[PDB]
Image (spheres, rainbow, N blue to C red):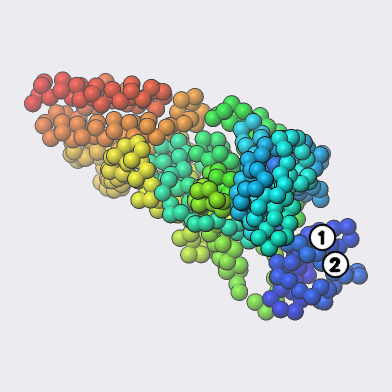
């Protein structure tokens, strides 16, 4: 029975674990399981129960973008005198500006048959995103009335729907949805299309699928911020929903000050215009932090319902991982996570959306797992955890050797390689999967050789093996390592990735061929083309990169004719 500011509840008669953040002297309505009003909930002064009919929900409409909110959709409120300068918690207010005049364009006409998910209108919310106005789930029937091409505010009725029962349902530019019931769809499609991040190591060796689940185990100082920001801005989604902001004391400060300056490199316009932030801080309660991921996923699901690909990005381990007094009859702590965290991840996916038209959207999840409390086994991983399908394992040792991104290629993995190979095969390069497999086998071989060498030295290493170490190094330096700060290498298109790969694998073939014909490895190592390959990541013209294959072959010919 602990807590001071708006939190959850504590039983009543049967299966009770559900309450509400209620203010204006106690208004703890929203019940996830219904009951016959006030019974057993009094602990402190007075304490009655005034329950409402509504559930723990979220407003979904034009006004989400650019907004910051908290665990439950309520706006910023900036306060002075703390860490950096700004400290903020959730203040009870309209989840969306009621004042704002939004521009409605009709996409339906009187007489049209509509179903849940049908797009009836459009509003340009920002200069990047077009907000699609959809019939709420579970409403079908005929369009009897519809607003004209005009400038309205959130609460206005833009359409009337006559259901087949005869009942008239009133529709506005927004809708409500219970944060903890997954928004419906026609069909969850199997993982098939990759979410192109533009990061070579990720797209090639540890790919994410649109609608897939990814985790980033983050040791302190591994370039976690950089990778996070790279993913957010380049990755193949139209909309980003971001949850965190309070893992460092001044994280809220930098979020408040820097975010509006950040630009979307795809359009030049500000990145905030396609983002919805959800802040989780140490000052903010607890209930608005347990419920935060559901608020996030619901808004993410809402944008995918429009036919968008959405990236749900979480980077708030500590604030989220707070425990609570649960003394009662019962099902264990590592099982209180295992129930909900699994259901949260179960809500990721690429879907055929609701609607009379065939339409697809997705929600992909990248969750940062960085603990200040040592290990990440039972504390923040124990579960079947097979629900997360890709791990990008950031690595401090790699970071201090200055290999970036510091993604450990031996302990990361992706179970989406077979799922996405066909897209790469059909759209970009028939040999993609064969090429990553080969490159991986070679990285894997390097790893064993370095262990052996460590134990016995490099003195007696044969030419074949030294060649494998040479080429493996070119793979690490020329391909895995990528420069987020460079104007060209901050993004690597699919077409560039496979070309760079082919250049490298060709050099390998030719290298082993040469050893095979008695050419010394030193002579191969000084080959001029070798260092041009070192710089191809900075080249923007893919054909100039491609020409390196012929250039390589030619130079090996100059080596062959001077031996055999």
Number of callouts in the render? 2
Instruction: Determine crowd level at label 1: few under 14, some 14-19, many 20+ residues with C-alpha closer than 10 A.
Output: some
- Name the residue located 29 percent from the left edge and 48 percent from the top edge: 448
Secondary structure at badge 1 equals loop
Residue 234: x, y in percent? 51, 35
Q: Which of the 4 quarters of the picture holds residue 17?
A: bottom right
Residue identified by numbered label 2: 50
Quarter of the rendering occupied by the N terminus: bottom right
The reply to whether callout 1 and callout 2 are in contact (CB within 8 Å) is yes
Q: Is residue 404 above or below residue 540?
A: below
> In this view of the protein, which residue sits in the foreground, 260 or 238?
238
Q: Is residue 403 or residue 108 the one in the foreground?
A: 108
Image coords of residue 186 (percent x, y): 52, 56
Q: Is residue 546 above or below residue 19?
A: above
Query: Viewer-proximal residue, 237 or 433?
Result: 237
Residue with the most extreme front position: 111
Of mark 1 and mark 2, the one earlier in the sequence is 1
Determine whether, in the image, residue 329 is placed left or right of residue 558.
right
Residue 56 position within the rendered picture, expressed as x and y whole percent measured from the top left: 72, 60
SS class, disc 2: loop
- Specify the quadrant that holds the C terminus: top left
Give the residue at the far right of this rendering.
Answer: 46
Front residue of 383 and 293 = 293
Which numbered circle lies on residue 22? 1
Circle 1 or circle 2, nearest the eye: 2
User: In which quadrant of the rendered view does residue 434 lie?
Assistant: top left
């Amino acid at each position: 029975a602990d807590g001071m500011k708006g939190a959850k509840m504590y039983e009543v008669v049967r299966v009770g674990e559900l309450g509400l953040i209620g203010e204006i002297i106690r208004l703890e309505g929203d019940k996830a399981v219904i009951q016959v009003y006030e019974e057993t909930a009094g602990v402190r002064p007075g304490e009655p129960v005034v329950g409402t009919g509504a559930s723990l929900s979220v407003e979904l409409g034009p006004g989400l973008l650019t907004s910051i909110y908290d665990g439950i959709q309520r706006p910023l409120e900036v306060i002075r005198e703390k860490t950096g300068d700004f400290i903020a918690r959730g203040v009870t207010a309209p989840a969306l500006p009621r004042d704002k005049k939004w521009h409605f364009i009709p996409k339906a006409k009187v007489g049209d048959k509509v179903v849940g998910g049908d797009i009836i209108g459009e509003v340009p919310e920002t200069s990047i995103i077009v907000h699609k106005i959809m019939v709420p789930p579970g409403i079908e029937g005929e369009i009897v009335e519809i607003a004209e091409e005009g400038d309205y505010t959130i609460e206005e009725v833009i359409a009337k729907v006559k259901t087949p029962s005869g009942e008239i349902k009133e529709l506005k530019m927004y809708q409500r949805w219970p944060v903890r019931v997954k928004r419906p769809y026609k069909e969850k499609l199997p993982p098939e299309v990759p979410l192109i991040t533009g990061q070579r190591v990720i797209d090639t060796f540890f790919p994410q699928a649109k609608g897939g689940t990814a985790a980033i185990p983050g040791p302190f100082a591994s370039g976690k911020t950089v990778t996070q920001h790279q993913l957010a801005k380049w990755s193949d989604a139209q909309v980003v929903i971001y949850i965190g902001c309070g893992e460092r004391g001044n994280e809220m400060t930098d979020v408040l000050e820097e975010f509006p300056k950040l630009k979307d490199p795809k359009t030049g316009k500000p990145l905030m215009e396609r983002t919805v932030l959800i802040a989780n801080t140490s000052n903010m309660p607890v209930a608005a932090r347990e419920a935060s991921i559901y608020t996030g996923i619901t808004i993410a699901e809402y944008f995918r319902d429009m036919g968008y690909d959405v990236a749900l990005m979480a980077d708030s381990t500590s604030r989220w991982a707070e425990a609570l007094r649960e003394i009662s009859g019962r099902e264990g702590y590592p099982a209180y996570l295992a129930s909900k965290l699994a259901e949260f991840y179960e809500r990721a996916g690429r879907v055929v959306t609701l609607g009379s038209d065939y339409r697809v959207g997705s929600v992909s999840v990248i969750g940062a797992v960085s603990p200040p409390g040592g290990d990440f086994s039972e504390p923040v991983v124990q579960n079947t955890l097979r629900v997360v399908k890709v791990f990008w394992a950031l690595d401090a040792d790699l970071a201090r050797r200055r290999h970036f991104p510091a993604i450990n290629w031996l302990t990361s993995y992706s179970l989406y390689v077979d799922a996405v190979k066909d897209w790469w095969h059909k759209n970009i390069d028939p040999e993609w999967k064969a090429m990553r497999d080969k490159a991986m086998a070679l990285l894997q071989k390097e790893s064993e050789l370095q262990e052996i060498v460590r134990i016995v030295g490099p003195d007696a290493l044969p030419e074949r093996e030294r060649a494998i170490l040479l080429v493996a190094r070119m793979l690490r330096e020329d391909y895995l390592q990528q420069d987020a700060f460079d104007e060209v290498d901050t993004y690597c298109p699919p077409e560039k990735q496979v070309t760079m790969m082919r250049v490298l694998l060709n050099f390998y073939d030719k290298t082993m061929e040469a050893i095979n014909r008695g050419v010394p490895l030193e002579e191969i190592a000084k080959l001029p083309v070798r260092e041009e390959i070192g710089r191809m990541k900075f080249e923007r013209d893919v054909s100039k990169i491609r020409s390196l294959i012929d250039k390589t072959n030619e130079q090996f010919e100059e080596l062959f004719k001077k031996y055999g």
